[PDB]
Amino acid sequence: INENVNASKSRIKDTDFAKETTALTKSQILSQASSSVLAQAKQAPNAALSLLG
Amino acid sequence: INENVNASKSRIKDTDFAKETTALTKSQILSQASSSVLAQAKQAPNAALSLLG
Image (cartoon, one colour):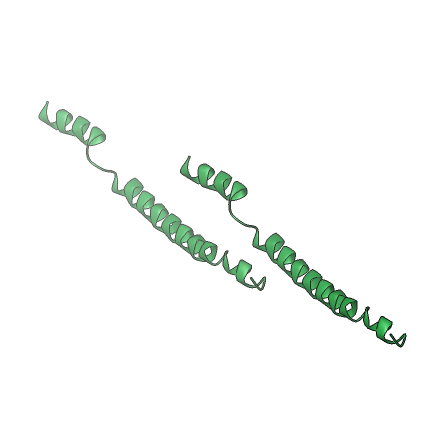
């Protein structure tokens, strides 16, 4: 009962390192993509300066 | 809600630098055109002096 109880607890509680590492890397790339788009969005108002105003 | 409220505020309150710079330039040209016509207007009465009077 201890073997099976621990196995049940693992399916519920312990992490799946194969799926969690994939989720981490996806969150990293998404962070860099949002940071890059944020960098270009900061330069959007610069267009108004080119209007001689 | 914060983003859509800020976009709505921009549409109602923030200035369009493309449309406003065009309105500023048009005003500058119209000011130069009115000033020029005024200059030629000041010399209109000088014609009376040309009538030996």
